[PDB]
Image (cartoon, rainbow over all chains, first blue to last red; front, side, top):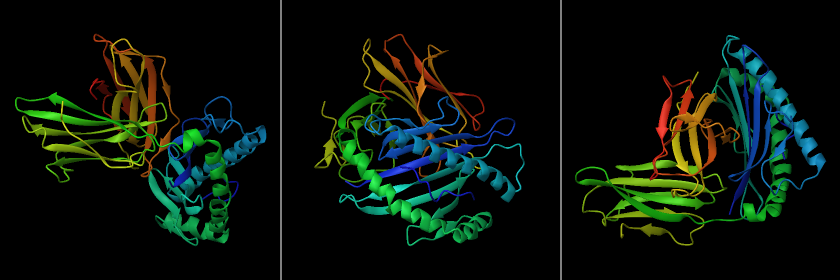
Length: 10
Length: 276
Length: 100
């Protein structure tokens, strides 16, 4: 299960 | 033993034409199980293993949407990073991200990772604690105040200690004969006349899982990392791995030496010798 | 900015025996950047029917692939792996040694 949250642009 | 999950995401810019290459992949320990590839036809997340397949068509839908968001995120990143480093539009650049969780044998959360690289090199990672960041330089010190203002750490903590782990067991529980197996190595050893009076002794380890394994030499009962050769553990194609360490010796001094193996699969540490 | 040349290993999935079925692998590790070219040759002729794994990466961020192809060893047959990378002057031909 990959994350729908975190994972933002730099 | 302890287990884990990792996701690997890579994006590669193609300056002289196209949008960027995007590949994703997931591993439960050393077994791949899912994959997305931008270039390849379907534009879906695709099962890569047999045990994962059973999940219904909203598992895959969700995964596909989420995976496309990541890839839009890396799309913007590559261009931002050009911004940060005043780089030309005519190089090709690379963003990898990696994350996932470790569990103990009790199956409970053990640790978490989240690490980001640009052009092969650490850019920012979170530290293994109540959550802070490590910025490789002043360009990434920027993504720091940026990610701190957004509470980005807390958002990942929640995923890593939360659904990452809750979901890891669902794959262990369901993929048991593929994932909870521990195959011992099928060891053997070969001899090769190479010179006039100096020969080779390769010691082979075939088809084992998991992939951790040590293979040491001993001239007369001590370690010998110098004068050996040790090829990096490779996978065989059939779910198991291969590996070998060899050693150049003098002719008629072969019984001196001993290949020592350690592995999860072995209750007891092994040892071979040029008997035949 | 940082380049890293590939490390190649060529080998069969099982131990070889003339005239039995087996898979021939070329395993390429430790490279950067990702763009790479890898053929499998038989008597120095590219073999079309080859497959390969989804690109992934190691703890130092360098990439690795596996390429493979069904085959039957024999005495006369000669098998190699040919490779190109942004770090390689000409290509790199690595033969298969039954005892490697």
